[PDB]
RNA sequence: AGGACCGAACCGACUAAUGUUGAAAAAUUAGCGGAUGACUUGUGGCUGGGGGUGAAAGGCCAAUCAAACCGGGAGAUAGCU
RNA sequence: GCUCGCCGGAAGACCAAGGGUUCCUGUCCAACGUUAAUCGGGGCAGGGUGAGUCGACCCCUAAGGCGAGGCCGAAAGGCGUAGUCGAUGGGAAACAGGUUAAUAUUCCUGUACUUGGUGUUACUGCGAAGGGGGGACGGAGAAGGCUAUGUUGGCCGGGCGACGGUUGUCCCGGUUUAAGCGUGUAGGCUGGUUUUCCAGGCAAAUCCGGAAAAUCAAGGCUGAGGCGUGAUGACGAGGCACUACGGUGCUGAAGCAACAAAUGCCCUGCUUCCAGGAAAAGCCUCUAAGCAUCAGGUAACAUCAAAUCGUACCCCAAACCGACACAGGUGGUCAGGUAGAGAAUACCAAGGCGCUUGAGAGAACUCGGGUGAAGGAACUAGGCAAAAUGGUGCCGUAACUUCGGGAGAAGGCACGCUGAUAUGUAGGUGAGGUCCCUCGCGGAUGGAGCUGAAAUCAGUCGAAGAUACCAGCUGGCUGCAACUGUUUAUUAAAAACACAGCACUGUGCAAACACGAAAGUGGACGUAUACGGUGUGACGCCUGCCCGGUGCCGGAAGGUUAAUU
RNA sequence: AAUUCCUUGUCGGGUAAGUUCCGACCUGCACGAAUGGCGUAAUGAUGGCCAGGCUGUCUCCACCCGAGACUCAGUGAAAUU
């Protein structure tokens, strides 16, 4: 649900928050935890390579089973949990043998549901099967680029992928960006979609909220001196040149894709 | 008003200590120059 | 509940007077702003000079910055005093 | 030595960092001390730092550093695996009293505790560079139960007043005691025991996880304080002999109760919220390869061992950083009385100081302050500076508005002391007695004693009762930026920079992009509801016409055009 | 008008008297719609203007309490020439 705070003071007038009472309120599963130290956007040379990164709240990493190769064993979900490392939620799953793992939470999954993976598995949300056995025209998420490598597509809060058609050992898919990509017809996928669509309805409402996420302020560039940025300075506000980034690239429509290694699985890039 | 020099023994040894100088090729040349000049105190070790 | 309210410790520096071979190579006295947060502080670590860092003034990098300090080319060149 | 003045959330007391004999005693006065100097942190000589329990070393690891082979690079060299280093964090054990001119939880007296080696005896499944448990963790808020500590009464010793009164409801002082061991309370968390079975924990497992039955609800764990012992002890106000009047032996009464109460303890607890809150070892368990009349394991007793280095003194300052015996700067711990909401402010206790040139005079002028006839901004670029407002309770309060605000809007009234209601009220605390009981640190009843607001009525003193310190001036019109924030250390704090929100554009993952001759690393252990760049800048109503020029994105016939041949 | 040279534009309000301030007019030297246009409650050690209270800011200065200046003893500088 979406709730808007009352205007008891400035900085809370425009705040809108998303609250989910179904999430578990307690400590997470200790055996599946790891440390994760901040970097500040600096590489092993000590120099800044990505700007506007620094600070924030301390976080711990949760191991998530993207591969999902446990086949032929039914499992039952226990509870949903809040993950600070990603926009989507996660679910704790207990297997029949007695092993526990973490998976991404689909849209219609709740406590007490049953899920399974493998070629024999049924066509129900939360089930993982090779795309060869998936009927065409269905919606899936968490797709693998190569067999056995792990999912790398449609992992965001409310993203999904639709299978268009298949001809041989390959399948055609439509991505959220609109691109039509061709992938091998042996990769795995999960039925349904990631359920957190309300994630995009939140509004921070104040500067401090951004700092909690570890985002530093941005300086425009037209407010600097010539020695710093191409946009330079001037007596007032002049800006008499074409828009450009630091280091001198147009960044107003110029394309930058120069891979050419594959250049064969792309058909309808976008637009 | 706070001034530039704030002493600290641990930091002094780690920056200009005898072992720090010997750990790098350029540092070893500093010792050679001072030895040739006949300095009585080679480093800040003591 | 709150980058909420009044106000000490703590962190800042808007006005006036004194001082200007000063007690002080930037302070003192009477008022002044924030004070649960984009807050403040101890110890150790990382980024090196056409480079670093910068909520952006050409600011800061050991009382030195529109290109730091030390040694060397070096007795640079000076139609000028 | 007797008076006077100043600090007292320090200008008192104990440390870390840093310094390195400045510490104690004798002796000297050239130089050093902004003056003299018999004095000194000055010159010279001698003396002083005592640990199985405090700290370091030592065991374990974070950021990060180095790095056998290895990968990469004209040389120098760069990155990194197995490993090895690195506290600001985790890991066994001691308290009180006495003593030196100078050290002590280190010496002495009394009473305790921890970890290892060896031997004896009894009973025995032992074994890890492997598995599991544990260690192990955020912000804010709300109570209840306690202690440190303070006040009063009782008790014990002493006192009868330099000037009117003072044998009583009078005056002064004291009334202190640890670790350890035994007991397991206020309160917090969790349902126990037995049997059978199993695709999981890299092999194994009696351990952890999972499944199905049976049988009971009392099982276990954690836990401040109090009480007993420690203690026929130690300490103890004042007396009495030594006493170079610097100081030592001996002796030594009372040593209880009530009330108030922390920011400290129970609490790594409980409730609640979104930004979702280190690692490894010690420690407790499970087995593998092995070894099994051996070797090892558990308990009792005896005995031995616990090395080495630091320990003086200053430490908000005359000893550290500022060239100085310099109105400067510097992290942690302890927290008495009266008034008070208070760690503000005023006066004081314990304790410590009067700041290393003095003596006279009482001109102009400069500096820091007090008061003022009549007028009241006529001053000046400008109300600069100064004056003024200032507390608690009750009554009362406009335009406008995003309905939260504006608002402490503006403005008005009451405040001391004594007596009565009530020889101290409402409230809080709570003994004896009585009763109950799983008889214990228990429940119910019961009310003595102690402590103690506010209000009403009457009377009374002064010019003045929020009397001192302390402690908002208020209202009307208008430009700019929404707001809290940030900036030229040392002439500019703003209308400048950030900001939530909005739009365009790039990027399908070995992502765009950035640092690197390269290897590689960041982006990210992320995946288009994601990430980078650019402009605008909350919110409300809106954002018109122009593609000739320059840039960017597409197209393709024809013309022109490099190396090469 | 943070934009208007001519300019103290013209009319009205406030004052005994207003080159500033507030409200209208349009002849906009040389405003204009995301290098955004026009409005806006609250907020500000921000710019301009007007009132009440209050005063040595002033007409116009007078007296008093302290530290220097002056005299005696000890120590004993500086720029310049």
Image: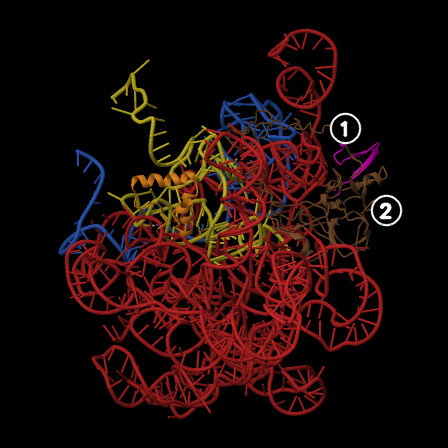
Chain colours: A brown, B orange, C yellow, D red, E blue
Discs 1 and 2 carry the same chain letter: yes
Name the spot of residue A234 as percent of width and height, x first. 51, 28
Say if D76 sits above or below D137 in the image.
Answer: above
State the image quarter where residue D99 is shown.
bottom left
Q: Which residue is mark 2?
A: A122
Say if B6 sits above or below D246 in the image.
Answer: above
Badge 1 element? loop
State the image quarter where residue D186 is shown.
bottom right
State the image quarter where residue D203 is shown.
bottom right
| Residue A173 sits inside the magenta stretch | yes
Name the spot of residue C68 as percent of width and height, x first. 39, 35
Do we see residue A180 in this rendering? yes
Neighbor class of circle 1 (other Cα within 10 Å; few <14, some 14-19, many 20+) is few
Q: Chain of mark 2?
A: A
Label tally: 2
> Which of D115 and A233 lies nearest the eye of the viewer?
D115
Say if D278 sits above or below A14 in the image.
Answer: below
Neighbor class of circle 2 (other Cα within 10 Å; few <14, some 14-19, many 20+) is few
Q: Chain of mark 1?
A: A
> Which of C52 and D75 lies nearest the eye of the viewer?
D75
Do we see residue A43 in this rendering? no
Residues shaded magenta: A158-181
The answer to which of marks 1 and 2 sits earlier in the sequence is 2
> Which of D418 and D125 lies nearest the eye of the viewer?
D125
Q: State the separation of the CA atoms marked 1 and 2.
A: 32 Å
Name the spot of residue D313 as percent of width and height, x first. 33, 64
Badge 2 element? loop
Residue A267, numbered circle: 1
What residue do we see at 35% from left, 46% from top?
A: B43
């Amino acid at each position: 649900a979406v709730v808007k705070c009352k205007p008891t003071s400035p900085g809370r007038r425009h705040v809108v928050k998303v609250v989910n009472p179904e999430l578990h309120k307690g400590k997470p599963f200790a055996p599946l935890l790891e440390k994760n130290s901040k970097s500040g956007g600096r590489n092993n040379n000590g120099r800044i390579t990505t700007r506007h990164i620094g600070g924030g709240h301390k976080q711990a990493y949760r191991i998530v089973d993207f591969k999902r190769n446990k086949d032929g064993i039914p499992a039952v979900v226990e509870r949903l949990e809040y993950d600070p490392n990603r926009s989507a939620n996660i679910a704790l799953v207990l297997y029949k043998d007695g092993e526990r793992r973490y998976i991404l939470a689909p849209k219609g999954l709740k406590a007490g549901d049953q899920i399974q993976s493998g070629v024999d598995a049924a066509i129900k949300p939360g089930n993982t099967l090779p795309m060869r056995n998936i009927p065409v025209g269905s919606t899936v998420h968490n797709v693998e680029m190569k067999p056995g490598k792990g999912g790398q597509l449609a992992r965001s809060a409310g993203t999904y992928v639709q299978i268009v058609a298949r001809d041989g050992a390959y399948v055609t898919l439509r991505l959220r960006s609109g691109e039509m990509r061709k992938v091998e017809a042996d990769c795995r996928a999960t039925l349904g979609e990631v359920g957190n669509a309300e994630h995009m309805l939140r509004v921070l409402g104040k500067a401090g909220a951004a700092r909690w996420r570890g985002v530093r302020p941005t300086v425009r560039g037209t407010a600097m001196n010539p020695v710093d940025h191409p946009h330079g300075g001037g007596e007032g506000r002049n800006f008499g040149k074409h828009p450009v980034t630091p280091w001198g690239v147009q960044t107003k429509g110029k394309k930058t894709r120069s891979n050419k290694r594959t250049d064969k699985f792309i058909v309808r890039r976008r637009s | 008003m706070k001034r530039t020099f704030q002493p600290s023994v641990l930091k002094r040894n780690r920056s200009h200590g005898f072992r720090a100088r010997m750990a790098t090729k350029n540092g070893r040349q500093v010792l050679a120059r001072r030895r040739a000049k006949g300095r009585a105190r080679l480093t800040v070790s003591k």
